[PDB]
Image (cartoon, rainbow, N blue to C red; front, side, top):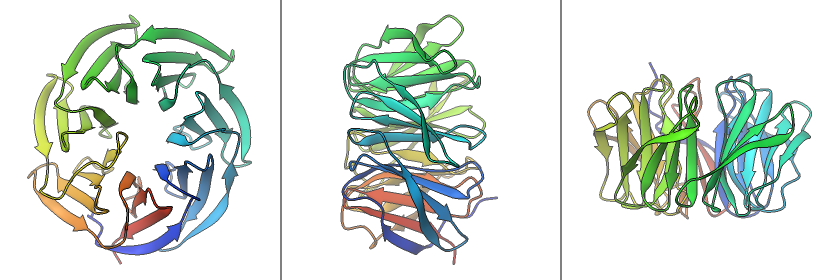
Length: 301
């Protein structure tokens, strides 16, 4: 399976200021970080080391989300400058700027058809983009400022300021369900099987939603776990067995999805609030990035 990390193996200053986004490449060889300093930075991940490779430039405001495509060839980043951008990873080249939103873009994701992008914005819309034709396909009023989006082959799920998760049927391009939670939605993540939806909300609760029944399977909480950001990001481990979230006090919480219990509280490496976490697809590392420039790679020594 995957093993819960135990100790910090690498600590480094990744951005000039706040780090908002972090993701591993599908092959676990690259780490991408995204900051308020407007750069996506790529880092080569070694078993126990991490070194700077280069930057993906073009954004005029902070980076809010990062996603690799399934091939690991392309990287998609939303920005506070109202655009999303796509670069080819291997040559650092900007390939697309997606302009259209009239407010900060808080999330952008590849649909599972290798063709299209969905983005969600503080302008209270989702936009669907065709990358081949270089156009916005469709703009939909989403009821409330959108803080995160995730995609299955059937459904787009978006999380919002108004505490709702909205479920959009891809085939009928329409809303088919909404679930209301008890705090602003800060993040969403799907498990590897895309059968369960993980949410984080500003009531300081993580929830796992069974996508078959649209019911709450499990919650995760802890006395010291508090969101530090309206965009505190949380993730499943690559086997779906654990969930990870960074806290406002700088600790990385890991819970067991089966038992519901806290497995680890990884502390004493962040002096500021953790904004995002990522779990490498190989299980080699868990990374946390904070408001004070820092990335921490946690692993089993």
